[PDB]
Every structure is written in C-alpha cells, then in structure tokens.
Image (cartoon, rainbow over all chains, first blue to last red; front, side, top):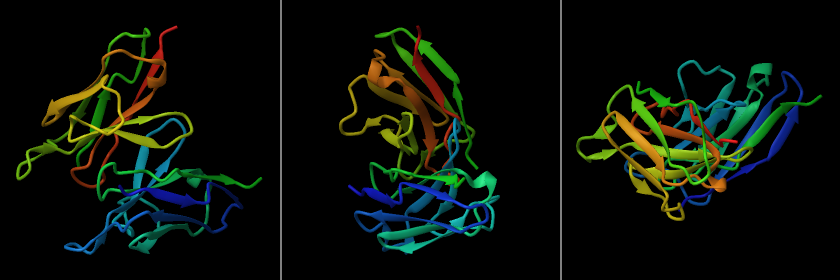
Amino acid sequence: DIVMTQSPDSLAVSLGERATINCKSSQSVLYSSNSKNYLAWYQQKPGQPPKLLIYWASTRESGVPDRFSGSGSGTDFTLTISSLQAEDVAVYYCQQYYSTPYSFGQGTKLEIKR
Amino acid sequence: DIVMTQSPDSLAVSLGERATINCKSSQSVLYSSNSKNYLAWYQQKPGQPPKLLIYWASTRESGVPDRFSGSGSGTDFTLTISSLQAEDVAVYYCQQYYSTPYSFGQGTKLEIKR
C-alpha cells in the first residue's frame, strides 16, 4: 500500500516569507496509462474540513491563490507557498489517491514565526 | 461539482449506544461502468490525519472494527457505529472521490454524552 512521509512536521516562518513542504510516496503514484500523478494537497484549518488545493500534483483548484504551486513526479513532491499570508496558516496534507487506503501524509503545521 | 451535506453536525450519545451519520451528495456518485459508489468515510481525531474507514460506500478498511458499517447508493449514504466505544469519539467525514474537487462533507462531531 502506498504510504506518505512529509517533511517537515511543523514550520514557523515570517510573514511574506517563502515556505515549502515535501511529500515522498513509498511508491510511485504516477499513472502510466495516464501520465498524471495521483497526488493532491489539502489545507486544513481548525475546526473545518480539508479543502483540495491541488490535484494531479500541480493543477491548482479554482479559487486557490496564485501563491500556491505544486510540483513533483513519481515519489517526490513539493508544495510551495511563495509568500506566507495570515490566511495561509493551517495544516497541509499530501494524499495519494492512487490505491486504497488513499493515505494522508502526517501533515505539516505552518504557523507564523513570532 | 459534487457537494456533500452531512447530518447531524454534532452528536453526543451514550457509551455502547448506536450512532448513525447521514451523507447526501448533491449529485450521484455511482459509477455506471463500475456500479461502485465513489464514497468514502473518514474518521479524524484531534491533531492527527484523516484515516480511511470505508471506501466504495460499504467496504471496510483492513483493521477497522466490525462495529463500523457503511451503506447507501446514489446520493444517500449512512455510517452506523453499532456500539459507540471510547476509541470512536472523533469527527467523521464523508467525501465523494467521483470528480474534482473531491469534496469532504462538513463533518460530524461524535462525543460521549455526559
């Protein structure tokens, strides 16, 4: 079964600073008939549900700021926030939707370094 | 886009009592070539990631207690906990994985009625 490991666990950064989050799948999530990577990134704020940010590794969802870009192929993926804004403080999850269980990574906490 | 509405929002029940959670998709999530319902149920505890419980509406994941069963077809689904145990207190999400965004329901909080 495909399992995900994110790095780092927690990340405190300055306002407007650049933030990156890695996601490693234990196995490739690239579909060969397809050439799409079955990798999605979720943003989760306190007391609300997980919201899709990006699917297919790099396609941004409608209404998601320009400042969020995904990238990667195979087993290695990255989420970049080009400028961390106060509305960006949340927990981010990578999840493979390649095969059951469609596992979430353990999440990365992003807070404003005070 | 397929959107999900769960009922109820919050539910406090006695220990060992039966609990049920409804999930209504705005559109059918039943695949016609397939006859599977692209409906999954997630259990989320505080400060951890969402864990798959059931996929295809009724198939339980390996290692998930007998006390969790899913049911439904089309637009109407239910999660039943046959006897609520102390390790069952969490937030439950239905999510359609039929088309983008693969939306989560707003979640249902299940606590022990004290």
